[PDB]
Length: 112
Length: 111
Image 1 (cartoon, each protein chain N blue to C red):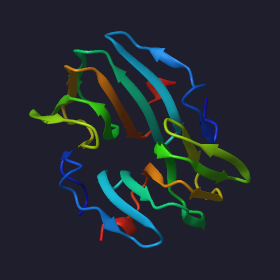
Image 2: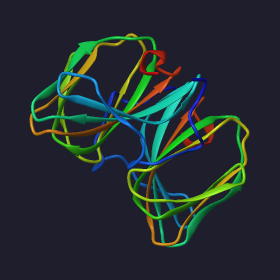
Image 3: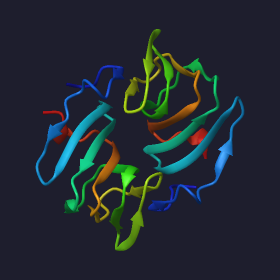
Image 4: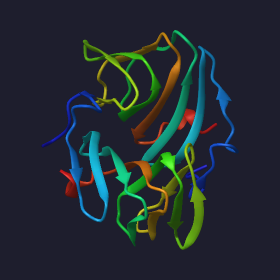
């Protein structure tokens, strides 16, 4: 839809079941910037992955095993990672948790 | 500095006192994307102001009075806002609290 409302309330915006133990909520977007909220079930993952979009991620809560470019770290609440364009990366959450994923271009795949 | 490390740690990243009862911590960036964490002291205020950068913001915790394009809303943990380029926006935090601000180009002024 080109862009989102200027305001979003966590309690109204639909939380979308995208399979794989993952749930996604739009926080706000336009053509060049986009932020979503992802809930991980215990042990859920984004299977190992790459894309053009720049990506910055923030751990809201839970323990995240994150792979960026073969470097591997365990991340907890308050931590973040950065994925350059086209860089290989992965994320696993054994405990369950919440991420804020932000991307520069928007991800057209998400705006269904 | 081009860009950040691929990994950043809440207990290690230096948190910068940026005056007005605001503090900022870098979460990760390159030329085209940037995410920072802002701590508001109780009653501290984010001046209304505009810029080309797109902005998407998430409220981690606290109560925020947020202005975008003159419309004002009370935001609490889990809510978010989006500021189109060059649109007026600002935020006041009566209770004290925490934001994540994300920008597309990077905010070159914050490095």
